[PDB]
Amino acid sequence: TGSTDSKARYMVAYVPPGVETPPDTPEKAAHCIHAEWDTGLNSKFTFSIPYVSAADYAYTASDVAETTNVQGWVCIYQITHGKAEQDTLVVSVSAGKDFELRLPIDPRSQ
Amino acid sequence: SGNTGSIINNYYMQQYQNSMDTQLNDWFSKLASSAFSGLFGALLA
Amino acid sequence: SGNTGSIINNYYMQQYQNSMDTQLNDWFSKLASSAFSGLFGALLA
Amino acid sequence: TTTTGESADPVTTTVENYGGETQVQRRQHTDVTFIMDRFVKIQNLNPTHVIDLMQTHQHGLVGALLRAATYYFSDLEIVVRHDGNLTWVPNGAPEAALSNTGNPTAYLKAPFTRLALPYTAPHRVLATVYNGTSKYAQLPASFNFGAIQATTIHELLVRMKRAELYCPRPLLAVEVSSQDRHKQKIIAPAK
Amino acid sequence: TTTTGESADPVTTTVENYGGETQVQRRQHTDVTFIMDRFVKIQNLNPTHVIDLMQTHQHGLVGALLRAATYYFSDLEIVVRHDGNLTWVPNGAPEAALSNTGNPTAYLKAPFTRLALPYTAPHRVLATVYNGTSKYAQLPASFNFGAIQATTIHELLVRMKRAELYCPRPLLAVEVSSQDRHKQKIIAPAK
Amino acid sequence: DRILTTRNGHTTSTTQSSVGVTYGYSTQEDHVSGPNTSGLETRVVQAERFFKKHLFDWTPDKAFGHLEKLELPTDHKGVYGHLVDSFAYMRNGWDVEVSAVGNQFNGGCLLVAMVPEWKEFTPREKYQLTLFPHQFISPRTNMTAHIVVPYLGVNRYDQYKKHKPWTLVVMVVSPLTTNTVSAGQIKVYANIAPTHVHVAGELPSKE
Amino acid sequence: DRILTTRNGHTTSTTQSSVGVTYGYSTQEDHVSGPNTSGLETRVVQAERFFKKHLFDWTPDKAFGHLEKLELPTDHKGVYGHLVDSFAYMRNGWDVEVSAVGNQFNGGCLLVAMVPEWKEFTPREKYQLTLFPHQFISPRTNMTAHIVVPYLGVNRYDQYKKHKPWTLVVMVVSPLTTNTVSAGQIKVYANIAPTHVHVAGELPSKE
């Protein structure tokens, strides 16, 4: 959402489970599945977080016992920018084409 | 229709089992189907 | 299939009675069928 | 995928963009008619009770999904545990009618009574929110599925049949303070 | 029959070698689906109970045969004798969900409740032994058929439907010390 | 034909005392591209080659039931080992050769088996280890056992740092016997190759 | 069409200010299977993906001729880097993207070039670096340069620990100018992917 005179280059990486902590730099994260893009006429970039797991389904809830996340992390980096100090990157999420939910449950406190 | 799985018909007529609709359309299905996919521009794969 | 012997169908649809398998094989039957029998050598019967 | 975000046109990128392959999906469990078609509790009861789906719990599976739609339509099934005979009257009836046998009246048969009822409102669809008044906040009084009465009503379950939902509205999960994930005890085998 | 034993190729000699005649055999009773398809007790119960087939008794007909396989798949039937209403939630549900009516809940009807349940694990098959850990001995917590809860659960029977077993493992009879045969009282008419 | 040459990548093994190859549970692999990797898996043929491990020394004092095991994968310092550290998920089968070189004047017998989901077997269960894919090594007949098994498990891909589906097991069936002309002990080695190696989910670099 | 998306393996890069792709010396690779590897070479597609490197900070004080270089391959902590340690010989080309993000109110110009067999150029030679495969980056026009080059060298396969055939060079042609509305400096980064990676001669493990 920056002004016309603000430019930036970003990177998003999907880090699967298997490392203790997420990479803190774009260089370490480059070895993961990732996409880099810069700002311009089209203000929006969309990226698919892939389903990569041992089992065919994953739990929607998270258990008290799991310390680091079972499905990995998404890391968003700024590679660099030009005059973009007060400018923002709005992030939203939607279901992908093969996203699927199964086994209806009624879990909230009632 | 819904959460029902009897292989056998209903003992009662439909005019009794449910209300009957009269006449004088899935918007979100159309909206989702219409979404752009792929890229935009020129690919160097 | 298994220990069931009703001559008559099930009142409920299969999608309700059981889970449905999807697709993307009897090893021991093959193994046993493949066993050698008879003798080996030359018989003087 | 790269696009004009301001236009707000739906865009659904896939893993094919970076060499993956989109899989098959089976979405029967998120089908609207299917998901609303199960019994849920009503809870705030009285011997005379007007059937109003907005009395379902706001975080319950059915109550939350219903509130995540602006307009809806459905037929209904109810299960009522009551003392005495149970009488039901349609939308629009004088409350006094609940005392008479000529209206659908179910004679007590343990453990409770289960009935199929038709939609009876005078409107083509009902709403979960209504921005205005109905008299010459709350919902217009005409948004109901009739009323029931018994000597005592101990429990009431409702089930939406052949439900139709229109115009999605916000649906919220529990708020998270953990800073990473909402964690809870997921069922797991003993010992 | 004479052969190379080291190769471990199956060899099935017959009485024909010395002039006998092999007979007809009918093996329906040792068919896997058939033999696992009967109810057996679970035994270690609590008002909140996660359905885990490994809680069958290790020497029981079903428990022993199940443990004589490495991987398995099946649907399930359960018979539960309980006080209060019985609620079941699928594999993966938060334990808290057991308190809500929107999940399959069976209202008490004497003498007990019998239900058919589908396999709901996220894995293509389950295992009776698992050589490793599942966290970031025991079996991974995801190896279950859901959980049930009632005020009190007095008895629980499970029945494997359309069972499939893979990779046989040791199955033991009682050990014998008699030096000749394990002897026991076989049923015989009175007087 | 007692002479067999096995090739895995740029490595070969030739044996003149084999009794054939035993295939366990299947003669082919399940599908390697299922929904759980979203088409992002790839094959790494550079990992499909033989690596070596000493298992134990078969001496006359080891009695029936003496059991030695090797869980797979094991520590690997080559290409296969780097894959375990660079990708979150993997799957592969195994091509296993076990050799026990003494001479034909030794007697005795070893059971060589591949066991899915290892668990410590009790003494009574050891009488039934032949339920698993196996071969025997008996000095009067062969010095080599050869077993080939596919990948298996509740999950289509695995995290080998958390779970090891296969375990190579060697058990003494009849004790090693010695003469004045026999060897005095037999060192048992494994020559193992991972097969159909697939990886998915590339990890970040550690630095 | 100023918008270009480049894909290398499971990594992509999208730029909205590009001036196309420059191919240097060829639009394809020489034969990767010659007599020197005796048919033992193999391709490693898991190495063909983008890695990143900061090159330098373009500030107003750097004058014409200021040159920054990066010899390839460089230290790589991923799959490609492991190949350099596991195989004696390798060959690959390069897919190179260099970005210099300031804003359109900056002025100045950078020369981005790929040079075979680097040698320190004298000041007079710098006037002729356009003889090498190159593109320019000028803030009024683009933020990205993109060059693709094949493997080359006197030898069909190389030992990268002893020789580096390609060097990425960035040289200031006209100094960075600033305004009240421009960026004050521009950080220059490289997004590089090795292409057609082939290895031969597997090495022993270090332990």
Image (cartoon, coloured by chain):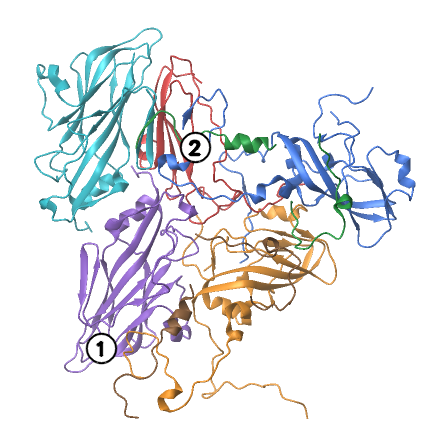
Chain colours: A red, B green, C brown, D blue, E orange, F purple, G cyan
Q: Residue at x 48, y 77 (%)?
A: E173
Near-viewer residue (D102 or G66): D102
Q: Residues within 10 Å of mark 2 (few under 14, many from 20)?
A: many
Residue G94 is marked as none
Which residue matches tag 2?
Answer: D13
Examine the image and state in which quarter residue F29 appears.
bottom left
Type of the residue with mark 2: Thr
Secondary structure of residue under mark 1: loop
Q: Residue at x 23, y 13 (%)?
A: G109
Examine the image and state in which quarter residue E130 appears.
bottom left
Type of the residue with mark 1: Thr
Query: Which x, y percent locates residue G121?
Result: 9, 20
**Above or below, comparing residue G92 to residue E161 in the picture:** above
**Residue B6 placement, left or right of G186:** right
Q: Residues within 10 Å of mark 1 (few under 14, many from 20)?
A: some
Judged from this view, the residue extending furthest toward the front is B24
**Residue D150 placement, left or right of G38:** right
Which residue matches tag 1?
Answer: F141
**Above or below, comparing residue D113 to residue E10 in the picture:** above
Q: Mark 2 and mark 1: span between their CA atoms?
A: 62 Å
